Length: 101
Image (tube, rainbow, N blue to C red):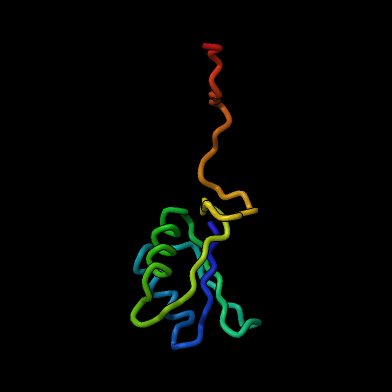
C-alpha cells in the first residue's frame, strides 16, 4: 500500500507521522521528502492500516498536528478520480442480468 503524509509546518514531521501511523498500527516503512517544503511518504504493509490511519489522522489532527494524509492507491472515491484504486479483484464472477425477463 502507498501513503502520502505531507504538510509539515507546525512541529509535525517524521516523528509526528511516525507516532501516529505506529499508534494506529505497524506500517511497512516511513520516509520523508526533503525536496518539498513539507511533504513525506509512508508505506503500509496492509491497506486496512492505511485506511484507518489516513482516515484518522486526516479526519482529526494528532496531538495538535494537522498533518495531510492521502492514499495513492486503494482509496475508492466518488470524485473525478482518474487513478484506479485497489479495492478488490472481481474477474472470476460476473452478473449483468442474463435473464431476458
